[PDB]
Amino acid sequence: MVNVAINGFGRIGRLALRLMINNPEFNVVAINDLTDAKMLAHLFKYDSAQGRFDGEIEVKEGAFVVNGKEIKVTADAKPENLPWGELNVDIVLECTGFFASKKSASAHIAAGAKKVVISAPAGNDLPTVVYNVNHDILKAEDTVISGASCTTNCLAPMAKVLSDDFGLTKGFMTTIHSYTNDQNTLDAPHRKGDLRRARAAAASIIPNSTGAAKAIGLVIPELAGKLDGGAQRVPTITGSLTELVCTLSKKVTVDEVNAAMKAAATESFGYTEDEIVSCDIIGSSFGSLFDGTQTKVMEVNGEQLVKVAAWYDNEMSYTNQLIRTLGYFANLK
Ligand SMILES: [Mg+2]
Image 1 (cartoon, rainbow, N blue to C red):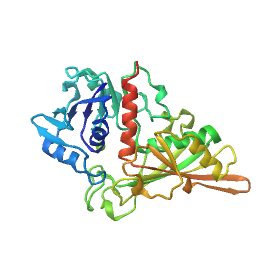
Image 2: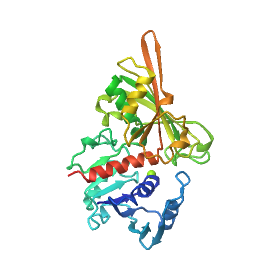
Image 3: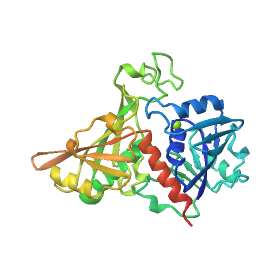
Image 4: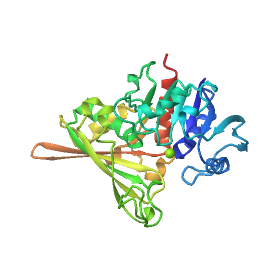
């Protein structure tokens, strides 16, 4: 049984607890967050995207009792002051967004935790892992790692098939992506100066920069620098689609591409030919759901261009991948 601490009870941290709370292989011992515990428990109980929490949560002084399990609730802004050694913390899920580097997140290790998984891209000086693409790179001596990004966890298994089976040479991604909380509700100044995230999120198609395709080489080294792309933020609350237009080293047909994806299906990478829409991915356990109905291959004067697409719940899909990686990493001996 792995002793887990959650730093940051935002959308990822709350869904992480939903996924772990009834899993006897995990012992969530602590949640650290600066927000009032009553507000946090209310946000855990009721969720506009994922629905109501199936069980029970009680608020105590300095703790929650969730489905009969007591979890300490702390509110310390500095990780090195957190009681991880005293709680025998095996691994921290770092979800605040404020420690997205190996150096900054290593403060959890100073506090007594043995390992850390950062729920975000966190640089290139640490292992960056998409479960069931490259978690075999992890070593027992590793300390702080990155679980990559939500979009990377959708893109990577599908790009890995295109690279392995067909020798992908280059490609552009478009993620048609649910809006996020760093977009404004109504038009207003934006904290980071982004003129597009300043706009009313639910009113428009809103272009936004991405990093997942450009950073793919940390997960799939043979694709380093071979992908680029961007996002279009649209008025859905969660649920997203990653499209990829690419060139390959081999000529292919639509059904050959789809067969290769289905052959690579795992608990992390699903395959469907159902004509689903984005709400149908909400709550999915897959990190990525390949949609064979969206595959296209075109050919002009003997050269092909290929288009493919996979669904992901940018919330729950990514968190499922984080928990797979967290469990695997903590049990590596
Ligand atoms: Mg979050």
